[PDB]
């Protein structure tokens, strides 16, 4: 592969409502965001049906739950600015409609919830730097001015909280390596300088926390295999060496922590089916990749239900949304086969970065 | 000690608001519930001042955050029934005032949030059985009728979610041993039979989840030392043997999981000071107890701030509330000395069980 | 129990030959040491038959393999001095007969192999202090003079190597607590002062190393339950708190590390049957005790065969030696039932310490 | 690199004597084996001086300690047959001189000690299959006839015991992948079929056991980085996926388990200096490679001293043997700088496999 490739992304963004019902957000052929939700917080639930938000959008939507349980969606508009819309009350299907946050956006938006309850949004700006904007009070439609964190980005940003409440942001840099920058005090506008984690990545970075607190980062490497790196101390400075796992993947990875505390990674494999690998013991070795039947046309998007069961969403060859899930709350559970969440077809609205 | 002793309890109940500010609830000499909160979600924050809820109460208050971020407090009233009051909006100091849930209550109330967003309350009833009542919709003032789970209780109940979303309830039985009962499917009114975990306990049980998912239970034993037992499988049936730790304790324990994923336990020690022990490695051996300066007159109540720092509340010999906290987000952090949260004096309103 | 009780000991000492065949040493009704060995290094092997060493002895024999593979046995003689005899070549049943090491001995002897290949023997002397004597060259019948390490002993000593090659010795002191003393440099006559590990023990201490390097010590406590303590650092100074396991035991424990690296403990239980407990995960919680059919009249002595399978020796009610073993090299293996190693009856020749 | 490359090997074979003194074996410019030993079992000991064994050899020597403590060396002779010579007594510098074992050898010999005390030798034969021969009684100069295990080898074989006593042998196959074959019962001539572990390796395999029992295998991969794979069950069939570590290495790796039970790997790095990586926690992530000053001309050979301290041997640019070691028995110890073990120069006598 080209060292500047960005692997295929997931086709929807997912969130858990305040009652843990899953709700998915995607872009249809009308260039509008449509959403659909479980009617009860279990993977075998029926889904409500696809519902449209009026308005044309020009990026993949990002969704996050506010600290008062209301979902809020962020998306680039036809004016290349940032727009958002929110549930007006937790677990209710009444939304505010799109409202402006301005700026000039050249990536998909990324959203993170600070540990003091304030949402914060990260984007690549018109100068290819990292910019951000935040709620000035928890779960309130009152936002800061736009501010730059500098750098040069060549991927979408990925943000995650450290165990001590400090946001850390990861992104590919101008040298195609993974860089990162972090708050030096929790939920405060005081940030480090940019630092390189060195390698070469060919996907957006994917970040998860392990049970020990520590962040782990997953990405596709230059040889098209999964690689990963982890924090080895109590700060954002001390990291392991990179490790790669054998097996060519053809999409971004998606990572999840199962209810036994072990990590699992899902990715589209070299044969265009869904592949899965899991840690066999704590911090442990990784299993050989296992394959699920069925050709898929996007990266997976992963979520967990109220009972811990993992559920995976993909685009099918018919350009509709399919999903499968674990049959039991159990690391060795069998899985269902792909089922259709029918009613619309989806397009990949991800911002083209070059 | 007597095998039917119940060790001294904590003097306040604490919760984190939606923005993670700590808020404490206690009973003053007027037999009313008073509360106080941090003005910002950090341990060195100033506190707002003690504010009264009108109404006379006859138990320790229990508090839990709803899935929409609103705090809700439960307490026994002068009529021996259950009463509750709630924040009318997340992170706001406007409350509903006490509203009735009826029933007949002979213990302190215990509250648990189901993984489908519904609060559920557990109490000992007038027949000494375990009774419960629940929200019929997530974060809504719409409640079920009272229902019995049977048994015979001689302690307050303690409830916790398993990793798969099933509530499990622990309580001392008529033989002074620890018993438990559990949902057999997550957030459903389908329950097991009562089963004994065998020993003899002389405090209320204290339950926490470890990073591996598994529940761990802590209690004082018949020889006045801390003992503990843990789940060793993926279900509620398979448990370890009990282990005891040397050192006489003179209150209920309080347990917390620090931001490195290790467990710590706090208790009033044999010299009436606060003692602390921590796991030195994963699942590991426990440290010798360490002592903090200062005589204390209750069990500790423990909480974590937005930046991970642990904070401990106790009754002082002056009958006021004192607290101390970690200076840094770090397992080996030093601690502050006791500081006063002045303005009222507190009484122990715990229901007397015999 | 009395705080100065010493629990019942094992009836034989066992060693692995250079080819890993098990060989057992015990004292018969003629007050002579007799031995018997496997004919091949597997638990289902036939045994050779009981063979006598000429000479009357007055303690339990201790056996250790030299660094050149020759077994060597140590025992107190009718003159209260230390005697030894050795295989004249590895894996051969030709022995030297008893030869004198003099001194005055008031405990059973304890033997440890230094990491420079020299045997070293620890005993309580006529002044109740700890004394020792060592080979001055590896696997050579050339010994030092007797030297005192001081202290006051009220149990037999137990010695074990730390991971860095320093011998550490454990023994009950005059206050019935567990004390210890250690080499400050590996395989050198340079020793620490005595230090207390505090509790009260009612058996000889039993010491094993875990996979992490660290020593763990097991003993019966004042309430007749198993207790244990472990090193938590890289030196001999830093230890955990003591923990107890529920369940009354009526003999010394015996500990072994199974081939998955987890610890298992065997002891005679409160019903006079053999009980077993194992660590369920690394450093983990301990299982409930499991019982084997059959009344036993000594503590267990445990060993491992060439294929990893655990084998347990006990005195039966007929005063003969019985054993059972794992059917497969596997932590969850089933076990055989007791089988007789017939031909002599055994007596407990342990030195009476008070 | 070429997929059929075999990376540069270590220049000496090392063993611990019965008293744990290190002794090294290498080939000098006269094509004879010379050896040198520590005079005391500590890394700062003086060495005795280089001593010659008479006889011309045509492979790297392999050395193993017998179960009676006597070292024994194996080497290919001028007739392409296998020869051996042994210490006539443990810890003594009197040797038997070279004695014939016949056969026809096309690799370096590899030696393994069965858990019943019998040495067993593995070689590639004249038909490129794996052949072996064994002692028919423990630590005795009585050997079996040569027997074939089949296969097709394109590297030297590497043998290691599983925790249950079964020998397992690893070697590169005709497809440049790593293959293996194993005893199906401990120390018995009953073997599995050959099975592939799949990848492509460009060094001999290096095998070590972890504390959990399980084997781990390290090799250089097709992209010249270190890769590794581990057993994930209790048998020889169940393995993890392969993982690679970033960093180009230019020699075979050498692995050792330090006294805290963690693995460390040493290799010549891309800048021709010695590099080291270690596991930061159990099973854990690996550290970034650290470099030692000094250009080296072979792979490292690693050993541990009687006090646990790691010591590393390499060929220097002057064609002599150099070594360095840890200053303390401690995972975070500093290291010495290279010191010369002077008196002869060494050649790489490894059999050229293509
Ligand atoms: C998402 C928003 O939808 C509106 O209808 C458009 O007019 C805005 O430019 C923006 O794209
Ligand atoms: C997000 C920011 O919006 C502003 O309007 C621009 O001037 C910046 O370059 C950046 O794109
Ligand atoms: C993953 C899905 O598998 C199914 O069999 C197909 O019918 C869909 O188009 C989709 O590709
Ligand atoms: C908490 C409630 O306060 C009210 O004022 C009382 O009248 C009720 O009985 C109840 O105790
Ligand atoms: C909580 C329950 O309230 C009801 O009114 C009573 O009849 C029950 O015994 C129980 O006390
Ligand atoms: C824990 C507290 O320590 C302080 O020194 C005392 O003044 C208080 O009364 C309280 O007992
Ligand atoms: C073990 C030794 O056996 C000999 O026969 C005795 O004469 C010695 O005193 C000693 O007891
Ligand atoms: C083992 C030692 O033997 C010597 O002969 C005695 O004088 C000492 O007290 C001690 O008993
Ligand atoms: C442990 C053994 O169990 C057997 O059944 C008995 O016959 C023996 O006497 C011995 O007590
Ligand atoms: C190692 C042996 O040395 C002897 O001197 C030679 O004659 C043999 O062929 C063999 O090489
Ligand atoms: C080691 C074996 O030696 C024998 O003499 C040969 O016939 C075989 O091919 C093999 O090389
Ligand atoms: C590793 C060694 O480092 C030293 O500085 C050099 O003098 C030697 O030749 C050798 O290369």
Image (tube, coloured by chain):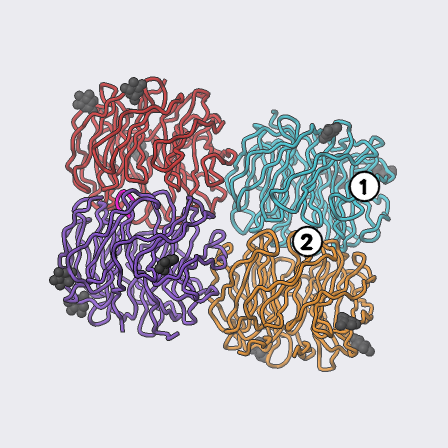
Chain colours: A red, B purple, C orange, D cyan
Task: Report which quarter residue C53 is drawn in.
Answer: bottom right
Q: Residues within 10 Å of mark 2 (few under 14, many from 20)?
A: many
Q: Name the chain letter of the residue that bears numbered label 1.
A: D
Residue A14 appears at what percent x and percent y?
28, 36
In the foreground, D158 or B322: B322
Task: Report which quarter residue D51 is drawn in.
Answer: top right
**In the rendered image, is residue C45 in sight?**
yes
Residue B230 appears at what percent x and percent y?
41, 59
Quadrant of ligand 1 in image: top left
Q: Is residue A229 left or right of residue B124?
A: right
Q: Main secondary structure of the magenta part?
A: loop
Q: Is residue D327 magenta?
A: no
Which quadrant, please, contains the C terminus of chain C? bottom right
Residue D295 appears at what percent x and percent y?
69, 27
**Which disc, if any, is residue D36?**
1
**In the rendered image, is residue A30 in sight?**
no
Residue at image mark 2: C165
Q: Is residue B49 left or right of residue B79?
A: right
Q: Is residue A107 above or below residue D243?
A: above
Do marks 2 and 1 share a chain? no
Magenta stretch, residue numbers = B16-20
Q: Name the chain letter of the residue that bears numbered label 2.
A: C
Question: What distance separates the C-alpha of mark 2 from that of mark 1?
Answer: 24 Å
Residue at 27% over, 43% down: B39
């Amino acid at each position: 592969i080209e060292n500047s490739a960005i692997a295929l992304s997931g086709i929807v963004s997912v969130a858990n409502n305040a009652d843990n019902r899953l709700e998915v957000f995607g872009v249809s052929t009308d260039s509008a965001v449509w959403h659909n939700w479980q009617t009860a917080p279990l993977p075998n639930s029926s889904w409500a049906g696809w519902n449209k938000f009026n308005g044309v959008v020009t990026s993949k939507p990002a969704v996050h739950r506010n600290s008062d349980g209301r979902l809020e969606v962020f998306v680039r508009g036809t004016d290349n600015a940032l727009w958002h819309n929110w549930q007006t009350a937790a677990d209710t299907n009444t939304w505010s409609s799109w409202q402006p946050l301005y700026g000039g956006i050249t990536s998909n938006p990324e959203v993170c919830l600070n540990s003091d309850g304030r949402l914060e949004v990260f984007v690549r700006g018109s100068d290819n730097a990292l910019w951000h904007i935040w709620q000035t009070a928890a779960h309130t439609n009152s936002w800061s001015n736009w501010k730059s964190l500098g750098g040069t980005l060549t991927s979408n940003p990925a943000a995650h909280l450290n165990a001590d409440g400090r946001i850390e942001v990861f992104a590919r840099g101008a040298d195609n390596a993974l860089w990162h920058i972090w708050q030096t005090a929790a939920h405060t506008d005081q940030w480090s300088n940019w630092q390189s984690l060195k390698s070469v990545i060919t996907s957006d970075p994917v970040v998860i926390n392990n049970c020990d607190g520590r962040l782990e980062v997953f990405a596709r490497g230059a040889d098209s295999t999964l690689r990963h790196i982890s924090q080895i101390g109590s700060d954002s400075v001390s990291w392991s060496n990179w490790q790669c796992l054998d097996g060519v993947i053809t999409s971004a990875p998606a990572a999840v922590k199962n209810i036994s505390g072990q990590l699992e990674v899902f990715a589209r494999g070299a044969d265009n089916t869904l592949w899965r690998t899991w840690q066999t013991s704590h911090n442990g070795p990784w299993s050989n990749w296992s394959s699920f039947t069925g050709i898929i046309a996007s990266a997976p998007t992963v979520a967990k239900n109220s009972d811990g069961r993992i559920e995976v969403f993909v685009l099918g060859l018919d350009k509709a949304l399919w999903h499968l899930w674990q049959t039991t709350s159990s690391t060795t559970s069998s899985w269902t086969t792909w089922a259709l969440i029918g009613g619309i077809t989806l397009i990949d609205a991800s911002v083209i970065l070059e």
